[PDB]
Amino acid sequence: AYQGFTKLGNREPLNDIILWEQITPTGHSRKEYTPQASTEYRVGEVLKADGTKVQAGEEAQADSVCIVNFYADLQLSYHGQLKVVGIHRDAELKDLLTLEASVDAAAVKTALAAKGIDFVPTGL
Amino acid sequence: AYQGFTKLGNREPLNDIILWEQITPTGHSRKEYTPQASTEYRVGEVLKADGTKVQAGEEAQADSVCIVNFYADLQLSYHGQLKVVGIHRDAELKDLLTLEASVDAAAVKTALAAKGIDFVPTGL
Amino acid sequence: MLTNSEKSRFFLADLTGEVQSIPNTYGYISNLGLFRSAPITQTTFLMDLTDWDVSLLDAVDRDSRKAETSAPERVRQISFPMMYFKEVESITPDEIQGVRQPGTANELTTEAVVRAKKLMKIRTKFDITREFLFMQALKGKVVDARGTLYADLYKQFDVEKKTVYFDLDNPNADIDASIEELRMHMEDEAKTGEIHVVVDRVFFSKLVKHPKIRDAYLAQQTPLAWQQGTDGVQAHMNTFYYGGVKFVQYNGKFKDKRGKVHTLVSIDSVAATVGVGHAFPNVSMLGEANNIFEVAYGPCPKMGYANTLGQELYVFEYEKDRDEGIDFEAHSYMLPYCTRPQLLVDVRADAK
Image (tube, rainbow over all chains, first blue to last red):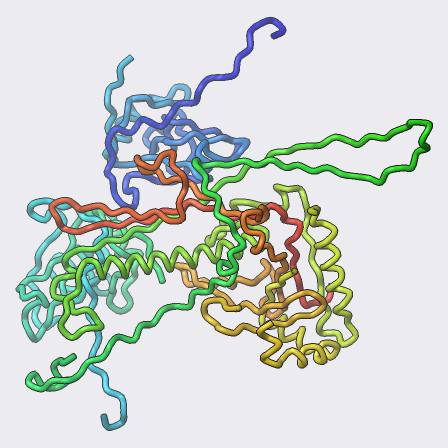
């Protein structure tokens, strides 16, 4: 190509965070959120109770961890569904959280630990 | 018969409400009550901690959901046992509650939901 | 079969079978079989749109050797999402221990009977949902029963919708003109190398009351003429044929979990008192060549079905540990659509 190099992008992260969850007929451990306008979601993000991402100063309000990849322009998840999904209780997750700038990871972990969510150390 | 019509009775509700309960060797999710005198018990009723059925203003005191049909005059349940069993925690049930007159359903559901009881939506 | 009398333990009585009662299950659209199944191996599918135009030639002289040519083709692509349905059931010994089945005096209920009953109920529910979704797809908008929008064919294919108004309440109104308008629109906009209109009760009554049509209507009342269809509930549904268009009265309706009643034949934001109907062409006889109506099917999230062909309905069974009961599950991943949305026309019995 002109200037040689061409790039086609990287692969999006896959949904493999879950190690153990309370399997039940009604999906006891999962909750669904309506996606906010002009926002993009990816696996490993922390959502507030209203579906908006947790920012600095409100770590105590952390509610759930994102589980799907969502595209703003399409308004459609990578699996062709209309709503975002997040785990909010009774689960064990890989320690691969993604947090906004200046968000205290320890505070978020403590807030989520109250709801029965535990994080397993992850290797390099 | 004379006047034509003759009616023999109706089926009492069967114990099929439970959709999921935490099976344990000693019934982790169940409790037993001593029935009060001359009160009929049918599946779906809400019982207080003392084994008496919930009434208006006692929603916050809701304790368990009855599961066995008890015959007042016969003094024993339809399975020939002398105690009333009610679900206590960690279960999912059909939305078929039986509530006394003028008893709010939302308050009872919120009270029971705090103990780990969820209702799977159902309808006809 | 002998059974204890109604007021004596020592005198017997003769029992008779049970009297079943089942809710109405309208299936007119599904019975026609004009929707072709098309299983898919993943959660999303695509399609290609093609079209070309032709024009008359011009007569050129033999010796000049002048010739003509034609314009090239054009292509386009589309995408579609899909809808997921699921419900759960359970069976435990408490429903089988010492429970006499209704149809017998002594015979005890067993696991197989309850399993069959629950499976039949689930299949009936899924069939009713299928019929509702098929009607919604024919309306031109695939809207979930709770109001969510999943597809808008008119915007997808870049085409508007036509509506034909019948002034049935006006004695001087013209019906032939409206029928011809509908027919000519359908013919012109088909764009390809038998018209049915599903009509409401009020619309049908208004149409057949008109003085200019009683002469034709009364001549068709002979039973020999009618025989020249059933919705699954009525074995003989009103039908009226005029001007090469067949009018059918469809009274199907269903109830939501909230008690809200959904009439199959209706137009959004229109009073029920106003006659309403939907028109579409009949394509069922084309069979394997039917490329206008199709239904997609996808796999379920289960481990053993990640990348397999879709199915009409999945059923799974699981134990509850320590033999305390059994669990059932039902899954479906379906989306109906029409590839010629311009052929769907609304019909109203009110002036402009």
